[PDB]
Length: 159
Ligand SMILES: NC(=O)c1ccc[n+]([C@@H]2O[C@H](COP(=O)([O-])OP(=O)(O)OC[C@H]3O[C@@H](n4cnc5c(N)ncnc54)[C@H](OP(=O)(O)O)[C@@H]3O)[C@@H](O)[C@H]2O)c1
Ligand SMILES: Nc1nc(=O)c2nc(CNc3ccc(C(=O)N[C@@H](CCC(=O)O)C(=O)O)cc3)cnc2[nH]1
Ligand SMILES: [Mn+2]
Ligand SMILES: [Mn+2]
Ligand SMILES: [Mn+2]
Ligand SMILES: [Mn+2]
Image 1 (cartoon, rainbow, N blue to C red):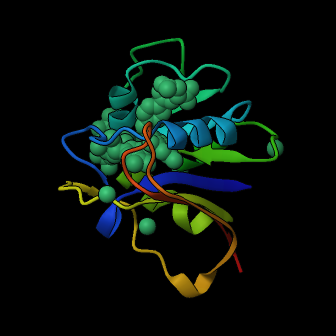
Image 2: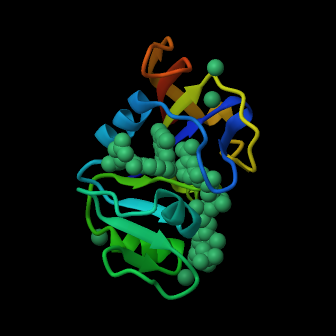
């Protein structure tokens, strides 16, 4: 099974200038909780944005060019990325925009954080078709001293 996990600001913005400008520790904790001990697939720009391997996960990087770091696994196509995960229950696709576009048609589950924040951005999560997806979990949180925006954690499963 393939799942996508992402945090979306208003208008499905996910990034600006190869960064995420907000800081929501509770959402990073949710990301870790849902990805630990699973393979994670990311594109090269997201690898550079994170800037180091994510511990406790098999890190697989998509790039058309040869890899430059043997602490992670480098692959050259979608099918190779999936194969490099092996026989696991759940593969997590962690972006960015271009990568999410390619894996969306293959995904059964979306783990989305909707952040109440207006962000100028240059990268968006794919327009997906709402009729294709059933919301199976949602949990809203108001802003607090550690998290400066309200946010909603949602899990959607392909109908
Ligand atoms: N809010 C969130 O949840 C979230 C999550 C992830 C990322 N982001 C943000 O998203 C932005 C990065 O997204 P992006 O769309 O610019 O880039 P991306 O999807 O991370 O990376 C694109 C790169 O991945 C490689 N690639 C993708 N598909 C490939 C394929 N089928 N075969 C071979 N290589 C392939 C290519 O690398 P080469 O050029 O080397 O061939 C391509 O240039 C940043 O702002 C980041 O902060 C946000
Ligand atoms: N829900 C969600 N939120 C995000 O912010 C997110 N970001 C990315 C891409 N960017 C990043 C940037 C940093 C880390 C990161 O350092 N994660 C640590 C958390 C511990 C910490 O630095 O506080 C990790 O171990 O996963 C992960 C993804 C991909 N999917 C996401 N999904
Ligand atoms: Mn091929
Ligand atoms: Mn197999
Ligand atoms: Mn949203
Ligand atoms: Mn806000």
